[PDB]
Image (cartoon, rainbow, N blue to C red; front, side, top):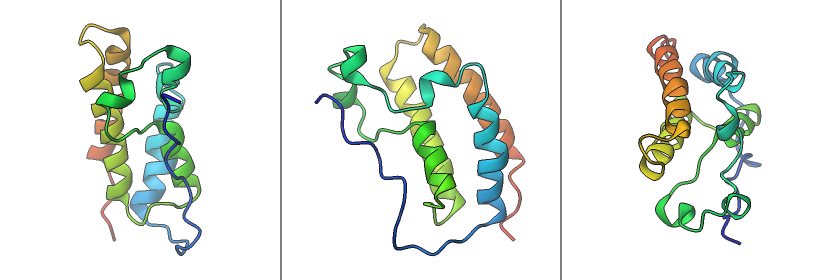
Length: 127
């Protein structure tokens, strides 16, 4: 396949532990971005086979998408909020390094990233 196996979304050997920031990342950040009208290209891994993108996974070193992030948050996969914020940043970076700067998809990514960054600016303190 041109497509890699999707990222792992659950960790069978980690304790269940919430934090205020992880709660915020699921209930405010992911929830807001997921329902946005421009979410759909980002709700699942890029299907390079179906879209016929033979170079996508040659260019992108670290696949990431909001479907994966959502499942990770729901499964308490992350030990800390910074891991989750990292995944969001990776997802945006992938879009911006692969897609042509004039492409609709980049516009969609920018709208979502603006919202993401606004919410991160209101991230609760880790206490």
